[PDB]
Amino acid sequence: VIKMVEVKLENLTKRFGNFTAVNKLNLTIKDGEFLVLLGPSGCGKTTTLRMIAGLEEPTEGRIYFGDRDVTYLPPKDRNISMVFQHMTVYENIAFPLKKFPKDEIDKRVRWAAELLQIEELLNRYPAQLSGGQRQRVAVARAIVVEPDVLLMDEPLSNLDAKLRVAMRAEIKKLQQKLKVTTIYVTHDQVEAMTMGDRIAVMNRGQLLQIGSPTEVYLRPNSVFVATFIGAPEMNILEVSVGDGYLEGRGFRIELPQMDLLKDYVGKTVLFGIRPEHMTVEGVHMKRTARLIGKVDFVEALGTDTILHVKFGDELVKVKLPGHIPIEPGREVKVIMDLDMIHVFDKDTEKAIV
Amino acid sequence: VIKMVEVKLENLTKRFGNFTAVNKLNLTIKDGEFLVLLGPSGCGKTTTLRMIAGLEEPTEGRIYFGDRDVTYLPPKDRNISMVFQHMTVYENIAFPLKKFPKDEIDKRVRWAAELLQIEELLNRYPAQLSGGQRQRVAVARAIVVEPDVLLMDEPLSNLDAKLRVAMRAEIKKLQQKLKVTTIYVTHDQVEAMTMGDRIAVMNRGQLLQIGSPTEVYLRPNSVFVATFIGAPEMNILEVSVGDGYLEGRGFRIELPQMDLLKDYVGKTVLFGIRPEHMTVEGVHMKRTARLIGKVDFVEALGTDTILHVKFGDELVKVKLPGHIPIEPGREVKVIMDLDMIHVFDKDTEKAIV
């Protein structure tokens, strides 16, 4: 049976010569949670996964599994399984069983196969695997050893959009049934939001923020996090703070008695509001702000309609549900939800909100 | 100056030995329109573009540009420009000018450069091209010859999501300014809906449907078209027609006196309703249908919340705007918009609606 193992990464650093790939990462991964490491290529998420697996050693720091320091233990002694990217399904799943009794091997294979709902493909071959998914087989093999920590590196990168969603759900439900601590690496924000109990956003080797999908989405602690999750991206506009309002290149926004910007009156800050947190007049929000503008372009995608509206000298995107192919040149009253607004220091790019 | 040239493809067929890549394609591309050829890999869209360009000859059929049969003319004599995928920007754009006067070359380069808003990068080099986009330069070069027909093959496949959207808009607006007949190939439905005045959906060498984004989205003439545009995909459920209702594996839907299914009462048809054309109770639609079900999984993406709800023995997706991370296991009253429903013959998969 599977255990719930807490994982601690302490002052973990990894520098390949001159390049610091991971800079003093501090993370406490809760026993049984599904943690997604989200970030662009080269942000350090993969290097971190590899250090957790033991395929790579840290330059500094420690890695604990429970109370055991596993920093310098071979990957085999850490009780982990990694998923990434002529035997029968039964043999494929059996392979990883490493001095094992034939009767123990059969019990586990059956258990894993049932968990992945592939019991009926056990005597079938890969190339023949049509009645199921070779994807599901790979997962059963990863969990067949009953790892204390499950590690996955962009396991779904090469799958059709429709099958990818089905796999996200499949993997997530399986992990919630097993409660095996899982560290999942992806650069895909939608996948991250779909699978992680928590998400750890990384950029240039640093942990920018960790929290639940709701926390990182509704309350990004910085511009980078605010714009890495949710597409179309959050509108970021440079503005100046006044008596009790914001003003940018060709517009002003009446700020209610928010105004946690006192230490910014007279200074420039970055204003942010998501496309989906705005709407157009004639199409509820407790507190709002209006700004008339002309539609510069329309993405009428049927399922959603994205308007590129010129705010004064600026250009922002407004996301409307459904098909509303309004034409370019027309003027619209853009309505902003004041309760969904963000404000970031222009220098540090950290949220002031 | 650019001309608006109507393009006719007549009974165009292309077979590579035994494989019919393009089967009797009949298409009248209007002068000055932006036509997108949309379809999966190997559907024939690329082969068609290549025949239009003259890089490939048809096995049967004719291709007209205006009144001229250009079927057997070298690509150079067809007046086309193709966009796909150490000179200065000015030189890059100038290259395609093929016995040209230096003073004519300068007028056109300036014109194209202004159209792409890259006039300030004219004396800059590629590797140095930081103040603009190498993408924009490629387009200026394609239009600098003033083609009668502009051809593009998945020109944006390798660009970050954010830059891709900016390019779609850039290319579309440019084409509307030039009114140059453009045939654009892509397997990306969102891009197709964004750029084409009309979209021609293809599958296995055949033209399944051609129409405006609104027409192919609201009225797909078949299951294939219905599910190739709009993601998450339209829910397709197998059902039987009755006195005045539909019934599937564990549910029934009261059909108003629609019922254009008289020739189907007692027979099985494919029912379809898009995730975005449904909603959940307690969250308007003129005519509706209700069905209580349990939430099997939730994609809480912040910008949208996709629910996988079990309809009787079936599983469908419901798309809700905003963040609504409702938990699995909970029961919900799913509300379907009866006016947005589709019905396809189960054998031919053609719309009956």
Image (cartoon, coloured by chain):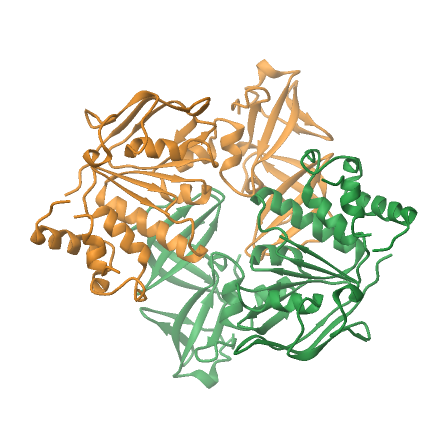
Chain colours: A green, B orange
Which residue is rendered at x = 42% and y = 31% of the image? B44
Tell me if residue B293 comes above or below residue B270 in the rendering.
Answer: below
Tell me if residue B29 comes above or below residue A222 in the rendering.
Answer: above
Residue B25 sits in which quadrant? top left
Q: Is residue B191 left or right of residue B238?
A: left
Tell me if residue A335 comes above or below residue A102 in the rendering.
Answer: below
Which residue is rendered at x = 53% and y = 66% of the image? A42
Please tell me which residue lies in front, A297 or A224: A224
- Which image quarter holds the N terminus of chain A? bottom right
| Residue B328 appears in the picture as rendered | no
| Residue B100 appears in the picture as rendered | yes
Extreme residue in the top direction = B263
Tell me if residue A41 comes above or below residue A23 in the rendering.
Answer: above
* Percent coordinates x, y for residue B197 in the rendering: 34, 38
* Percent coordinates x, y for residue B292 in the rendering: 71, 39
Please tell me which residue lies in front, B210 or A325: B210
Residue B152 sits in which quadrant? top left
Please tell me which residue lies in front, B110 or B226: B110
* Percent coordinates x, y for residue A153 in the rendering: 64, 58
Please tell me which residue lies in front, B320 or B168: B168
Residue A88 sits in which quadrant? top right
